[PDB]
Length: 22
Image: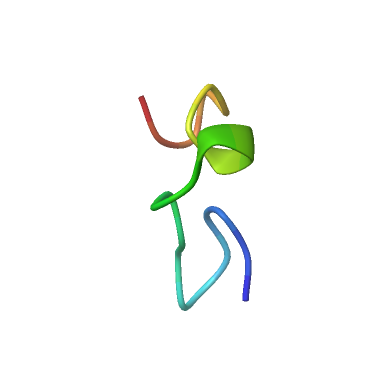
């Protein structure tokens, strides 16, 4: 599970600012 690696996972606060989400 990763903020952007398949499967992406920007459903958190520490994985949202990630240019790969916001």
